[PDB]
Amino acid sequence: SSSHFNPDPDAETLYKAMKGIGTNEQAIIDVLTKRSNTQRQQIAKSFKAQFGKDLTETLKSELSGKFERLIVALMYPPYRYEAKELHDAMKGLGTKEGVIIEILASRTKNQLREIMKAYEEDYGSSLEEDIQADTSGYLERILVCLLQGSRDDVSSFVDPALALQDAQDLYAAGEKIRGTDEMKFITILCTRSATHLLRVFEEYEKIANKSIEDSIKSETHGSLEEAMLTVVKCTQNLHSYFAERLYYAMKGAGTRDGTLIRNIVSRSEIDLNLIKCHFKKMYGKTLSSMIMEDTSGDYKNALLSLVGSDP
Ligand SMILES: [Ca+2]
Image 1 (cartoon, protein in one colour):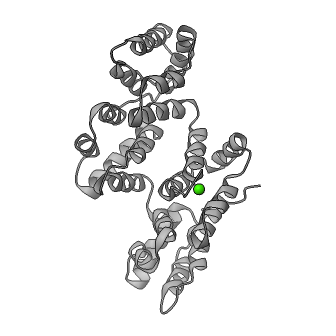
Image 2 (cartoon, protein in one colour):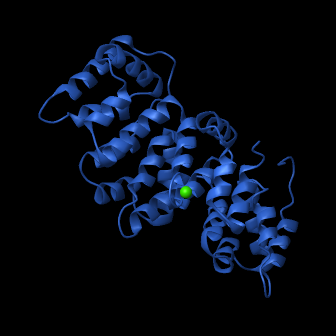
Image 3 (cartoon, helix red, strand yellow):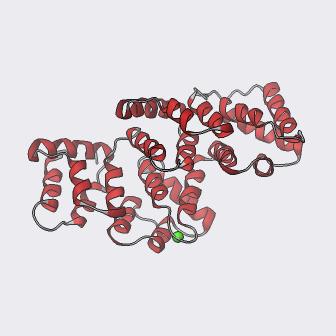
């Protein structure tokens, strides 16, 4: 699709869709959900050159509700999008700790470096400093650690002696009776590579006769538990993590639309095809069927256009 692209006609379609009295929402869906993010940026530039207004600001004014949130989300470049989500998680009343955990645990070091740069450019403060001020306790420690390198950019070579020592230390940390040693869990889970951690989880099972997930579930609670389990799930299979995130955004009463939007939008050009496959395998139904059950209107139709064919 990106073999060679003139954005001008698409910009004109959007102009006609919003100009005057009445809004053609379907024409907005047909352009923005069928073009790539980079093509959208070209469309935005053409729109401003031709018509003198910023496309995103125009979209924010012309549209409302969930449909507006989704369409505007599509207009953010990668990394800047996550920076906006993280800012929104902290700037309001309360902290949306779940948003922060998801992004920090599921992104790679190099992705996080880009998100950190975008966050400082757009909001004039350091992401790490804002997290330090807005969170506390052990949650604060793991989140800061995930940003503070927490690298791997790995090999396939794991040090077997260190993997065994890490597993021994995790076991010992769980076994202390007047307070789990949370810092030992945090350091190993946040500073070791994914490949090393997979071996640690294997060794931990042999030593402890308990899965690492069940140990975390019995030894921790609340946000710290969520954060640890998220690191574990992302290490084992990232695509499966995102499927589960989407499932729980929709399961039961109501919808966590913020979570649905963010995960579909941010994964749309990376692994949404694998997420769809994993969703089917894990839950015995398609992603689209749950979206159809939980959402309505132009919002629903835009989500389904993005997801694409889902037999
Ligand atoms: Ca629901």
